[PDB]
Structures are given as structure tokens and as C-alpha cells.
Amino acid sequence: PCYSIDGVIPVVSPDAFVHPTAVLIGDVIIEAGVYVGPFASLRADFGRIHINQNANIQDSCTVHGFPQSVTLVEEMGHIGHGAILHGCRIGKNVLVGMNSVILDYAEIGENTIIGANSLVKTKDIIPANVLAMGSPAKVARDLSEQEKKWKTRGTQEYMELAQRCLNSMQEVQPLSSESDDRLTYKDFS
Amino acid sequence: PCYSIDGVIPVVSPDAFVHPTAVLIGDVIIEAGVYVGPFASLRADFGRIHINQNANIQDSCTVHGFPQSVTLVEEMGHIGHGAILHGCRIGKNVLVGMNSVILDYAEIGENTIIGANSLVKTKDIIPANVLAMGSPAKVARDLSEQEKKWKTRGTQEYMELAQRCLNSMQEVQPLSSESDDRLTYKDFS
Amino acid sequence: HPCYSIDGVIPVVSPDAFVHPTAVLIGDVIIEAGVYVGPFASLRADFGRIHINQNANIQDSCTVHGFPQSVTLVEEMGHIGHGAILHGCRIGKNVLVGMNSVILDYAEIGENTIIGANSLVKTKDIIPANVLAMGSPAKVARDLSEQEKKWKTRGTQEYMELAQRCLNSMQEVQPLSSESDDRLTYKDFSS
Ligand SMILES: [Ca+2]
Ligand SMILES: [Zn+2]
Ligand SMILES: [Zn+2]
Ligand SMILES: [Zn+2]
Image 1: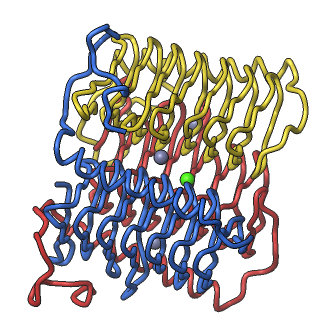
Image 2 (image 1 turned 120 degrees about the vertical axis):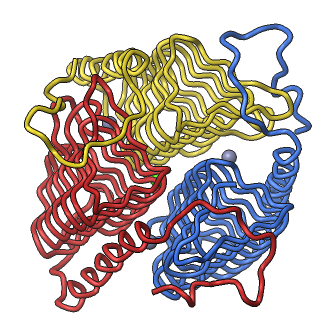
């Protein structure tokens, strides 16, 4: 799923999992432990994209930016389904809710959670350790210690998912019907 | 387009159509008559995903869930382009408007229509036979009898589409220019 | 070229358009010269027609669709941002559709207009030309400055250049397993 452009080749840590239906274009760098899910477009054809270690990019997420831009997800950044990151900076251990849009030059402080379906305006700087949501997103409150531990729990699970996928994910013919003896989600490691 | 993980293999009814660019991961069960469109990610690597008969999952939709979660689309569920289903229950004959987010433990009552770009918060229960929209989504009014018929029409077209795609959809090289005698949408059923 | 026919209807793609190999074109899609179509864009003309005029771009995970007998139209230099969804609508010349926006059926966007990200344009809405509109449901906000109009034009020019660059050099490649000093970087893009 990696494409070069102008001779620029993505860099993918051997310990990261890129689903074969993701797309990596150009100056994309993936550090160890990262999970890239189906139909994630990490398109570095105008600028750079760096996904730091133990981060995850989920289904049909898009990472892009303007010419000479740098789009950064710091480690354990957690990018929910359908979120769009544009020339922005995602701080360490941040959660970007599903279907959210983070615009250019925006920065999200460490541990902060952006609610689903939110829009962070261009150049907005969101402090660390808060919940921000809405469109455009506004800080709602401090995160509790409960929520912070929960978030880590979710991110830790995606870290395991990358390993599970390197170990066992493969193309298969589907079964034509349910069977009494087939493995199920209860069989999940 | 099916992927196993931890040896768990998707189940796809022979009478469903899964576009070849969709992705089914893990404990996904697809019943008869269903349509799954391009870039739909049915990612059952943490829990179970069940798509009941005559439902449709449209382009770049994502279905995911919590560990040990069960995400259910009931019969004739109608999941619009770009909508994201996360550990929720979609009632029979529901319409989830495009680009909408349905969060964990949420349930949509039978026949209800969710407007585009909406967000159903975690654990929210949307009643049957209503229109709900917004972010966060709220009930706006009862569905009309005509609106209920129009939705059913819409879904019947997707049930037909599933059959059309099993019958005739295939990879082709594109034509290099429009022509006077090439088949067109006027030739559709 | 990832094209699919349905009911024997075959997409039409100019040789001078670039369609990323992971896009999907279904049915009666007509792509003209200079268009760029990005990863996982679904142009699904299985109920109606899709026409993408020249020098336009459809970005990542964009979806284009429409109801039976509909004609969905992106005019010249139409600029459809990441994850936007167009449903049986009319995208005027040189329009910009913000990321993650939804443009519903019979909607028309007048030429040069900018739709903000995360916007929803309601069915049959006619949004005028040369304005900035945004919200869900979207609403006209004000006229567009000449600064903004030239801002947009350069961006679209960038995507016309991307089509060429991509036809010229985009290729399936195995990734490097580590950064290195000699590898080309974004500093080596024309920009
Ligand atoms: Ca979206
Ligand atoms: Zn972009
Ligand atoms: Zn998820
Ligand atoms: Zn549609």
C-alpha cells in the first residue's frame, strides 16, 4: 500500500502494522507499534507526515497537508474512524474522535480528547488534558483521571492490535454460513 | 476482501454483495440480500458485527466496536455514505444519514431516520418511527407515512442493487472518451 | 485503472486524468482531462450519471453518488476536499467543497464559492456564486475577498500539477524500513 512520488518513498517501521488497503504516499514516516487501519490515506505529496510510535490511524482516516507542511501525530496519538488531520500537530497520547477534522497549524495538547464529529479551526491551540468538542470545537472541561486511564486502555488495545495483525491477519475466503464450531470474537486473544 | 484475525473468519451469505474494495475483518456476519459498498470497513477485530438481511452499508462506511461488543444492523438497515457505526444497535429498517456517527451502546428504534452529519451519543436510545438529527442528535418529530414509504423505496433500490452487482458488476478498463453508442445510466434498471 | 461496469455501463476516463489505483469508478462516471482522483474516492454512478469536468479534483475517501436517473456534476476546477460527499448535486466552476462536507440532491453551488469544512448543504439548496458558506445546515456568511479567490485558485492549480506529477511518477513501491540521509524528502517536491 506504499506509493512513491517524485522518488520520495514512505518509511515504515518493521514493528508497525499497515493494513494492505491503507495508502501511504510520499514523505510518510511510520514509527514502531503504529496501527494503520483500512482505507487510511497518509498522503505526503505536498509536505511531510510523521506518525510517532504506538499511535494508531483508523479506518478511512485521512492525513494530508499543504506544500512544505509538517503533519505530526505524537506517540500514542489515537485517531478515530474517519477523522481528517490537515497540517496539524496531535500531541502525545491525544484522542481524536471519529469523523473529526483538525485543520492546519492547529495543535492539540497532550492527553486531550476531541469529541467525535468536531472541527478544530485552523491555527487553534488546544491545551493539554482537556475535553474539547463541537464544530468549531471549544474546551468543555478538564479530563478526569478516570477518562485518562480509559483512553490509555483504548490506545494500549490498538498497540496490541498491531501485534495481533502482524501475527495473524491474512486474506481468507469467507465462510458461506455460520457454523457451530467456528471461532468467534469470544476467541479473541 | 475478507481478512481473518486470531483465526476468526467472516461469514458472507452467497446472496449478499460485498464490493471487492470493501474490507471485512474478523467476526463479521453478512446475511442474504445485503449490499456492502466501496471502502466499507466492517472491522470485527474486537467484537462481533452482524449485518442482517436486505441491509446496505455504503461507501467509506465504518463498522467497529468495543472489545466483546456486538454491533448490530437489523433487517433493511440503511447506512448512508461515510456513516460510522460503533458498538451500537440499528433497528429494523432504519436510515442512518450520510456522514453520521452512532456511538457505543446507542440504539435507533425501528423505521427511524437519522439525518446526515448527525451524532448519536453513547448509550442514547432513539425511539422508533421518528426523525432525529443534529450533533448531538435530538428527536425532531414523528416520521410521516410518506417519509416511511420513501425510505422503503430507497432500501428496495439497494436490495435490487445487490442483485444487479452479483449479476453484472465486473472489473473493466475504462473507455478513453464518451461515445454516441456506449451504454449509459439510461440503460439501468 | 480501477473501474467497474454495471449493467454493461463502463466509466469514461480521459488519458490525461489521474485516478489513483485505489479509487473506485462504477458505472456511468465520466472523467475529463486533468482531473485528479485520490485514494478511496468512490465515484459510484450505479443509479445515475457522474460527470467530473476537466482540471477538477476529488480527494481522499470522497464519495460521489446520486439517486436513479440523477446527474451529479462537478464542473471545471471543482475542488472536492477530503471526505466530502456529493449526492446528486451541481458543483459550479472553480468551487471548493470543504473537507468532510455533505452536498445533497439538487443542491447547486454557484461558481467560485467556498464551502467550509464539515458543512451540510440541504437538498435543493441554491448557494450563490462568490461567497463563503458553512455550517450544518450550511448558511451563506459573506462575500469572498479577492485574496480568498486567488488562494483557492493556487490550491486547485496544485492539484492539476499533482495529476501530472502522479501520472509522471507515482508508483507502487516497498517502503524503506528506516529513515536515511540519502532518501528524497518533501524538500524534493516541486511545490
Ligand atoms: Ca466523514
Ligand atoms: Zn489536503
Ligand atoms: Zn473503534
Ligand atoms: Zn447514495
